[PDB]
Image (cartoon, rainbow over all chains, first blue to last red; front, top):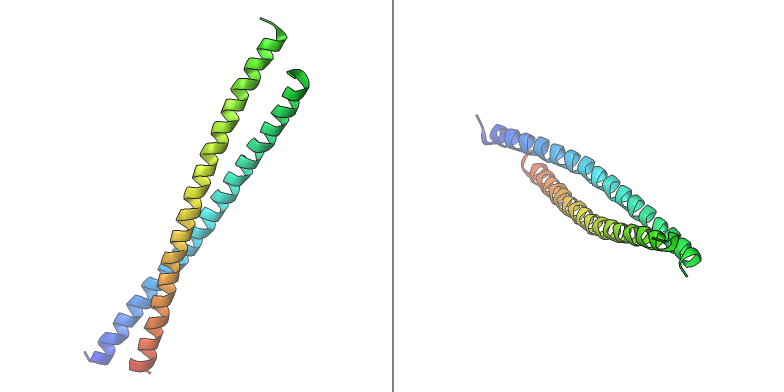
Length: 62
Length: 62
């Protein structure tokens, strides 16, 4: 009924919402770090493969 | 017709494929860096908002 209780509830709901937001965003951030690391892996593989191609070429086409 | 020409073509197709792979992955990596930076922004906002909530609370509920 009181301003105090009204505020206690508002603050509690807001706290819960922020905590969930922060928890979800942290998880999502982790997932995105992983997708980025994976893409670098694939990209690095492709660059290695490309330098192997050039070694092959310098030997058999030049 | 010759082994040489057959290999020239294979190497050329493979080079093109690797270049596109590397180009696409770089773009995707950039996009993922951006999504991650954005998530940190939102997450930081939420943490700031949370410490503002606690200041509000320490003043009006304690």
